[PDB]
Every structure is written in structure tokens, then in C-alpha cells.
Image (cartoon, coloured by chain):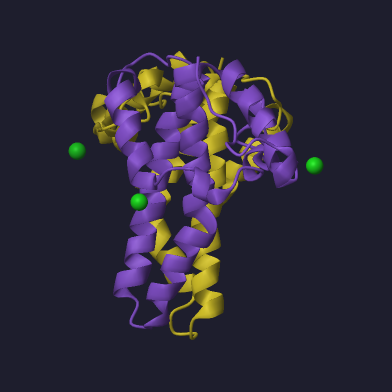
Chain colours: A purple, B yellow
Amino acid sequence: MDIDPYKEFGATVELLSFLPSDFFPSVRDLLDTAAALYRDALESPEHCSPHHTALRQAILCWGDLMTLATWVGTNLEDPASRDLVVSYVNTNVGLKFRQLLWFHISCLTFGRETVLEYLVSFGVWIRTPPAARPPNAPILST
Amino acid sequence: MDIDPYKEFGATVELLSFLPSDFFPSVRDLLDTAAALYRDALESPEHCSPHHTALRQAILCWGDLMTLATWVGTNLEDPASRDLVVSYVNTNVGLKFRQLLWFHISCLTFGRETVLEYLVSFGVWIRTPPAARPPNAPILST
Ligand SMILES: [Cl-]
Ligand SMILES: [Cl-]
Ligand SMILES: [Cl-]
């Protein structure tokens, strides 16, 4: 089987991958922000929206991923398990889940429709040769 | 925060934990049932249910778990192997993923409410002496 966590929301993995990695904030900064704003909504008994329903599972899934990454990097007596877990987290799943947190939090702050257009706008800007774009890349607001 | 993934769906971690860990099918079977019933709906871009939105996310991050497992057995010496990491996973979050997959799939097949009422009745039924219960077990259907 094969699923795109973004398809049901009107985006894809490729649309987010077209953003540069350094653009997304850290896993901890996103987690902090997700609490401060939607602490109350996330811990509620009402699916506030499919964005809330996705954000709860994603956040909990990542903690499962992080428990495993901890066990593998600490309790394997092979020393290369450190570098393998650091690589796995940076290279692979940390950035994949940094995008996912950012998408659903921004859809909740600026609305799904606003956020999507910002992707496509960012998409032309990056694809555009530098002397032909504005020095500042696009920016998200209401 | 502290997010119960069952709370927006009327249940709690303790209610799923109220059934014996023997009871929930392997993660592999549940994926097969999930792909055999809601493949096209889960891959659909249509939000089909808050259960759908949540099932999609659980499916993908079981894969992120097994992907890490693979790295360890591939990139490290064979005493630390994929079989070791996976044995760790299934000991840990393995049941947690079986309960989730079951709850959300079985909530799609039968009514959600059917499932919740089953959880309590089946849970007490297996705990009751044969002499002091009805002979026929609480069951799920429509
Ligand atoms: Cl971080
Ligand atoms: Cl392109
Ligand atoms: Cl008991």
C-alpha cells in the first residue's frame, strides 16, 4: 500500500520537498508552538478538523519514532549506532516530520487555502534564477 | 501536552488496554485488512472519515519504524540486526499499533459505537467466570 499524508489536505510530498530544508524550524520549536496555540484544542474530545486529527497522530507517532531512535543509539553496543541514528534523524525522518508539523500548524493558523498558495508561490521563487527573483523569498500572512 | 489518540473518538487508552494483548491481530494482518477494505479510500484525497485521517498517519509511521529497523541490520554488524530492533519494536509500541489499527479499522467496518460498546462488554465477559455469564460472547456486527 501507498499513502500521501498530504493528499487528503490538498498538497503532496513533492510540493513540500520543493522548499529548502533549512526553511523549516526545529522539531522542538514546532512542538512548542503546537502546544502554545492548540494545546486546548488538541487535548479535546472533538475532532476540531482533519488537521487536528492528523496533528495528534503525527505528534504521537513521532514520539514512538523517538523512543526507538533513543533505544537504538544508546543500548546498541555497536558504536556506529550513534552516527546511524543521528544520520537517520537528520537525513531522513526528522526533516520529513518537520515539514508535516509545519504544514498542519500553518493550515490551522493561516487556513488550508492560504498555506497551499504560499507553497506554489515559494515554488516559482526557488525555481527562478536569483537575479530574476526578489532577494527576499515569499512570506506567509493573513 | 498529553494527547490521548482515542479521546476524540469516544475511547481511551485504558479502554483499548482493557482487552488482553492476546486479542488484537498482528500489525501485519491489520494492514492487510486495511488495504483489503479501504485501500482506495485511504489513498483517496477525500477525508473520508476522521478515522481515515488517523489510519493514514498510523500506517506511514509504522513504516518509519520498520525503515529504521532495516538500517540497523543493514549498516551494523550482524549481532545487532533488523530482527533485534523489530523484536524491540513489537515489545514496545507493537501492541499500541495493533490496538490503534484494530480500533480504527473495526470502527470503519462496524459502527464506531458498536465497537465501543463491544470493548466494555467483551472486556468484562472474558473476566467473568463461565458459570456467571451468558454462554455466548459479545460480538461485533451491524
Ligand atoms: Cl531540535
Ligand atoms: Cl517542476
Ligand atoms: Cl483485571
Q: Residue at x 42, y 80 (%)?
A: A80
In the image, A13 versus B16, the foreground residue is A13
x and y, in percent, of residue A92 in the image? 54, 58
Decide if residue A33 is on the left or right side of residue B99.
Answer: left
Image: B131 above or below A17: above
Quarter that holds the N terminus of chain A: top right
A28 with respect to B43 (left or right): left
Front residue (pair A51, B9): A51
Between B24 and B66, which is closer to the camera in this rendering? B66
Q: Please name the residue shown 30% across and 36% down the image.
A: A32
* Front-most of residues A112 and A43: A112
Q: Position of residue B69 (x, y in %)?
A: 50, 66
The answer, for residue B23, to whether it is visible in the render is no
- Residue B40 in view here: yes
Position in image of residue B27 (x %, y %): 52, 48
Which residue is painted at 32% across and 22% down in the image? A37
Drawn side of residue A113 relative to residue A62, left or right: right
- Horizontal side of residue A11 vs B70, given as left or right: right
Q: Quadrant of residue B70?
A: bottom right
Q: Residue at x 41, y 46 (%)?
A: A62
The quarter holding residue B10 reads top left
Residue A132 image point, x, y percent: 75, 39
Q: Is residue B44 above or below residue A86?
A: above
